[PDB]
Image 1 (tube, helix red, strand yellow):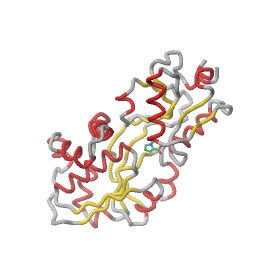
Image 2 (cartoon, protein in one colour):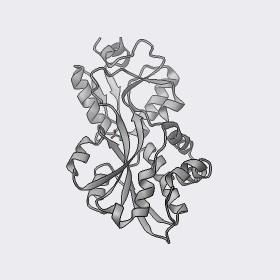
Image 3 (cartoon, protein in one colour):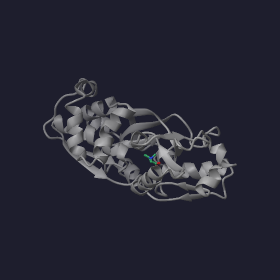
Image 4 (cartoon, protein in one colour):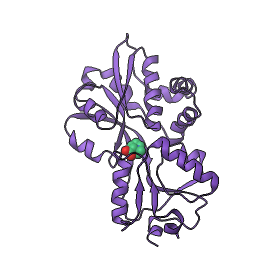
Length: 264
Ligand SMILES: C[N+]1(C)CCC[C@H]1C(=O)O
């Protein structure tokens, strides 16, 4: 059984994260209160995944779709019939209150930013290969010529205007923040990227100390953070849809398909 196979253990990421709260709810929804959820981090969990995959050792992680892990590995979602992880998750483009009128040109670009999951992986994979994000961003924009035209449609050039982009250091958001960062730099902007945790990121935006962020995962991941700063930020675009999250096992675990299978 799945309980037999993993010793009632889920390998997760960092404790302060959205997927970890959501998992807490999951374990509670499916009556898994004798299970152990290991907190770790992205780096640590993906390493533990690597060990177990190679050995064909059964493992249950907390996975999220917009990530290179589904590329480097044959993985799968355990079905969530109780939808503990919510649904219709999206990546959003947020700014500080009154950025759109302070800088109409920069907001135009930010609101027009869209791309797909594998287009983001185009970047994420090269970065995990050890390529420098700023180089991969440049390579990307000088490759996907038509996509940038979409984004920069009716967008003027500026004389060294300053812009502060706040990002949370998940691999997905290193992808997006750099690509957009580069687009702005090609446009003649003085671009700063400020790294922060989620929370400090939301605060920075809500208190004007950062201009924009491409790290808002709504509505499920940052339910609380979005609520907390309800009338104090701008949501000016969706940069991606169909992002999924939950319990992920490798495909070799044929007999484990639902979270329900853990009750056995
Ligand atoms: C799903 N994630 C791992 C990726 C971005 C948000 C983060 C989380 O808080 O769960």
